[PDB]
Amino acid sequence: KLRIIHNGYEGQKRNQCNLMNKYGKLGDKFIVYTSLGVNPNNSSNKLMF
Amino acid sequence: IPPYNLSTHGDERWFKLYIKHVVDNNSHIIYSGQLTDTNINITLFIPL
Figure 1 (cartoon, helix red, strand yellow):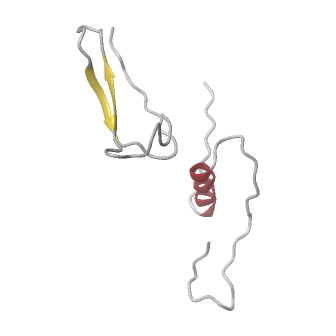
Figure 2 (cartoon, chains in turn brown, orange):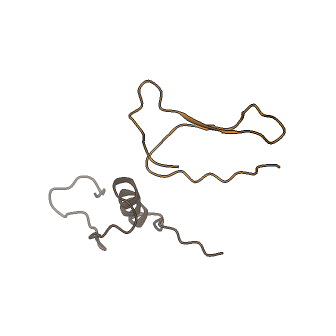
């Protein structure tokens, strides 16, 4: 019995992955982004979209 | 189980699924939960 799951490694991957699940169906085709960084300028957050 | 449908929530969002004809002709309630996007995978044991 084979099991294939779309959930992200806890962190950004899971968030991106949950966006994929929430706003889209499987087999749908789209762009995702590997590296996310906080800006040196314009940020107070240490947080990222 | 599908995300949201046939219609919108009004009046009530919730979905319940029943069992019937096993020992009794009348239906019996085996699961009750809120309907939510996007997918719900429920695995049940059903007796014969």
